[PDB]
Image (cartoon, rainbow, N blue to C red; front, side, top):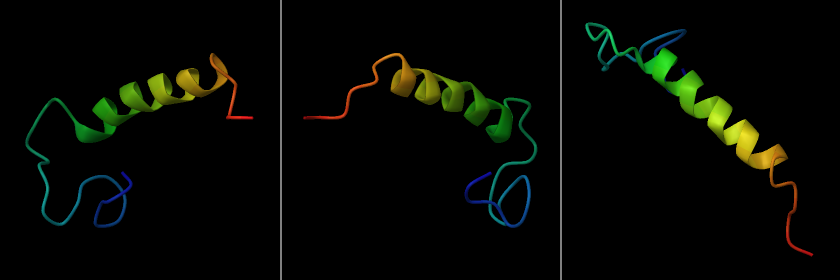
Length: 44
């Protein structure tokens, strides 16, 4: 995670959920990476 204690979950986070914040993030993370390349245009 980008705001965890060390690796997975934060000191104050939710480990008990099956949704999984790391898993949920990698879902959004790919959507972000796609949004960049599949619309490759900054502002010029």
